[PDB]
Amino acid sequence: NAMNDWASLGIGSIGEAVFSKLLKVVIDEAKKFKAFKPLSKDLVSTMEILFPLTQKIDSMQKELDFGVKELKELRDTIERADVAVRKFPRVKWYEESEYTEEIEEINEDMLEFCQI
Amino acid sequence: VFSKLLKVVIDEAKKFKAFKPLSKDLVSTMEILFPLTQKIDSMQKELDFGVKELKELRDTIERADVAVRKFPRVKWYEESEYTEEIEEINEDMLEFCQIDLQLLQHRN
Amino acid sequence: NAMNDWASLGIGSIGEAVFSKLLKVVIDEAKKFKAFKPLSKDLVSTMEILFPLTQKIDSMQKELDFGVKELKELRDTIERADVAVRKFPRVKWYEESEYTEEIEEINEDMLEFCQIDLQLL
Image 1 (tube, each protein chain N blue to C red):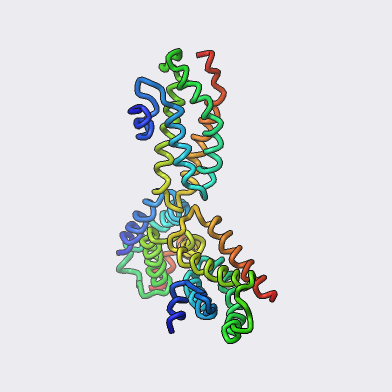
Image 2: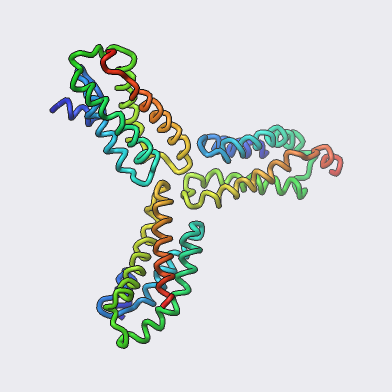
């Protein structure tokens, strides 16, 4: 509906969560960059492991208070991921290592966000 | 004729001097294949280009053509992916450098 | 001053010496490419250690024969650094090593100019 379109734009939560639809968008953009493996491979792998969790985190929202620091951070981390694959076309050869670290941090954060 | 077709690709690749696989690896070994490509044309009537060996040389010589032509658009992330592409073309071309034209001539 | 604006255009000296002002534009420009360490880290380090020498040259220029190998080549090397850093937006990914060799060379020359004793004129 509406928040589904907000999710396409990269906004994961507006006092309600559509994390599942946002993660699908991020996965589909990162899948496009076959040759950059930190995206196409590592991130798209660890993101795909979280897609089921987000599916459930979408069917059961009232029970949880997304106010919790960890829950807020999950949206924040998923939006960080979106703004990072979206800008990959504009990333310069000299920014490879800088950009790779960023993608790796977004990778690490997302994993510990499944230890729960 | 296709000695000419090797020249146009020897020409384009030499222009990108800083990228060694093109300017120091491929063009080094398109240069050995150059006298031989010339000889093939001196013998065009006698030889049958229908032969598998010559057919492949046409295919590799254009495979090389597409790669050098498309270089200006290879993005930094596509580097290693591209370096194998041409270093696999540079493989097939080196082994073409070690052929007996006389053997094919004898085989009609 | 008009002299400082000339330093900004990449001029190191007209009659007057402006080594320290020009060397700061080149530090600032080099600082813009934070991700490219040979520029933003390696070169800026050397340039910062050269900066006090240039500052002294600028204050005591009334007393220096600027027609000497050492002072002319310093000025020239600072200018060499300027066009080398203004040129980075146009180096392509397959040129990284050539550009790095160019910068490493300027870096070397700029370090060597730190040995200068300003008193020996």
